Image (cartoon, rainbow over all chains, first blue to last red; front, side):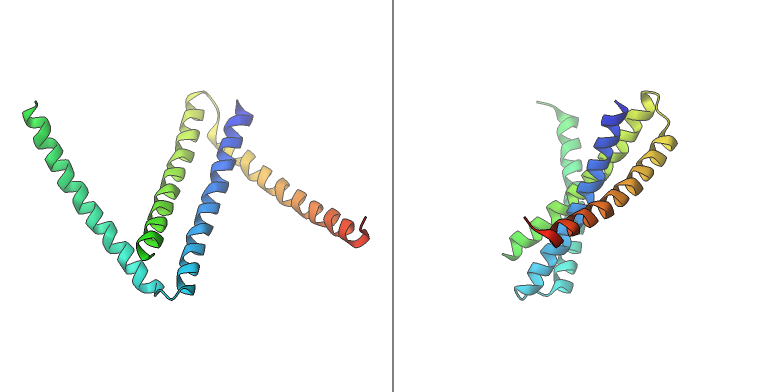
Length: 70
Length: 70
């Protein structure tokens, strides 16, 4: 068990690095095809805000649903 | 393309969070089965050092191989 718990942790730690590299690669590939990376980052930030607001709206709709039933 | 590049980035960003949570879960599960987390972390750190030293040794063996051929 210890060996397995430890290996799971190490594999997850490795995947996290891998994923962080890939993000950098995707930016780089994008810059190479002509996209402005600074604009992309702003766009990603704004989507994150919109997604947050939609999640609040969804939570409210959901409550309304639960408050009424079938 | 932009839509796809952006979605790839967002999905990777999400997976990274997911993976960071899982690591925390694995620790927590371990603490719950009786393991000492502080000891585990030291062990993980020492394996990382050993793995680094093995990687250097492997790089040297590899060079020796390339320096001789078949």
